[PDB]
Image (cartoon, rainbow over all chains, first blue to last red):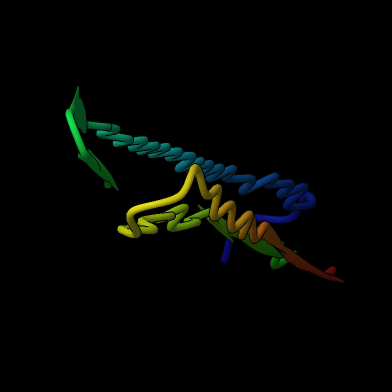
Length: 49
Length: 50
């Protein structure tokens, strides 16, 4: 037999990281206006629309 | 960690008016009509969760 001593040591370490970000924006605007006026006058009538 | 953000907005408008005046007679005559309308709508909703 062999006399003596055994000394053992260990360090196991890990690391993991994950990040994700999403952002969206959509804007739609519409405007529509149409105008018309007519007018007529002759002896002896009057029309205005 | 979790994060959620939602915001919605809707705007709508409407405006219309009809003005028609017609008067026919032997003597001088006048007919006038005035109509105008306006609509406005605004909606907003926001949500945030962490």
